[PDB]
Image 1: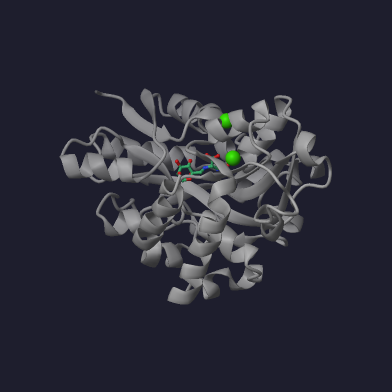
Image 2: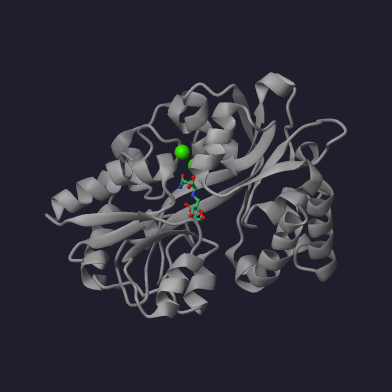
Length: 326
Ligand SMILES: NC(=O)CC[C@H](NC[C@@]1(O)OC[C@@H](O)[C@@H](O)[C@@H]1O)C(=O)O
Ligand SMILES: [Ca+2]
Ligand SMILES: [Ca+2]
């Protein structure tokens, strides 16, 4: 009840944040903290709506931020919590501080397809060319866009296509056509990593760090950055946080280059603080696994928070219908 409560999505990703950021920053500030886990920012909304907020810091996505901010779920962060020039443009708002870049990408089972696995969203959606069990997230960010890409939309026109009612309906129709081949709608990064380790799916759209972690654990899977979504993860403080002031100081400390440099030590993620790269001096081998590496960025498209700030409610309901058809 006296400790700052920080929450992310568990598994290897939470363990990496706790080791590189939370435990060293709390030690430097001589403070005590408690961890929690959640999969959707709507759980932070529920706390705000119930009138009993227990979480202080929440780890959310860059495209969750406009929605959460509009719903009054987030506190406004103190000015100069970070220097905006040290982070990618748009990754730091008045209610969010980025901690990393990651990819929502295609991974496939080498026992099923060998080296000849799906290398694009058109291939992921091609049950004729690639027969097998698919796994998709139970939340729509990266999933609606995957269907738009599968329909032939160029990566740079994804959100131009999803700007019309016609494009949005076509993306849902493409997901509905794929739905009978979707054996599991994964709910957490650790569950997606477990599906990969057990070879329970033939192909999956999930986060790069989770995929690489499963492969490091022995999974006979391969993956590509082609047609992947370049995402941004970060921190926000819950509106009415019981330890708001202490949380603000903790978030300021953990955003520093000295902690950020250690974030990809074992977990395949890309630090958001640009000064971390100079401090750590990552090997080319290390850089190649990073979502934000130039060669990887070249075959990706960035998530658009402006799209999600407008059509999240529609996407949630329509995507729920696609999954509820099973
Ligand atoms: N930054 C990273 O490298 C990790 C990427 C990825 N994070 C995705 C996430 O932030 O997306 C929005 C929310 O669903 C979160 O629960 C989740 O941790 C993961 O958990 O694997
Ligand atoms: Ca994991
Ligand atoms: Ca990951």
